[PDB]
Every structure is written in C-alpha cells, then in structure tokens.
Length: 84
Image (cartoon, rainbow, N blue to C red; front, side, top):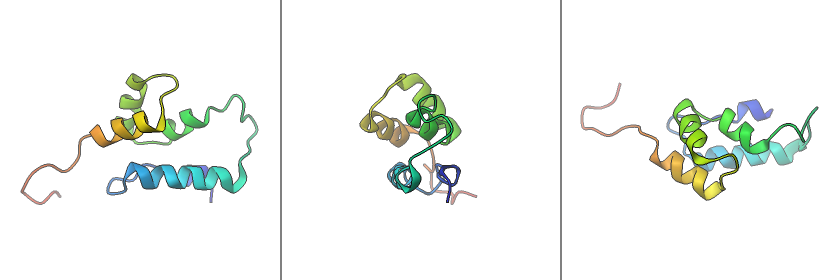
C-alpha cells in the first residue's frame, strides 16, 4: 500500500501507473521529506528504466501529458512472433 508498489508495469499502461501513483499519494500524501522529495521524480524514479531515460530527456518538470507521451513512445511488443 506504499508508493513503491506503484511501478510501471510491462503490460500495464502509464495511465494506470499514474492512477496508482496518484492513488497512493492521495492515500497518505506525506513523507519524511515531501519538499525535497519530488513527486514527479518519484513517478519517474518509480517508473520503468526506459521511461526513466525518456523522462530524463523530457525535462526537470515535464507535464503529465509529456510524461504519458514519452511513455507511449517507449518501445515494447511490435512483431508477429508471439513475444516470449
């Protein structure tokens, strides 16, 4: 029931990931250093690796739209041969 549980699933869309992130955040919006703790940085940090890279390129203060746009860009399943 922690924000950690909020991760960027493989088959899970970024939207669902954000919903969870914001769901847990609002579940107990608080931390030992919320100020120092950049929520956005948490989502990105708690986000996949590639997304992290894409988010890194994004900017130190991208918008949800930009975050979702980059996430949507992230690679994935793109072929016939059923992925492992």
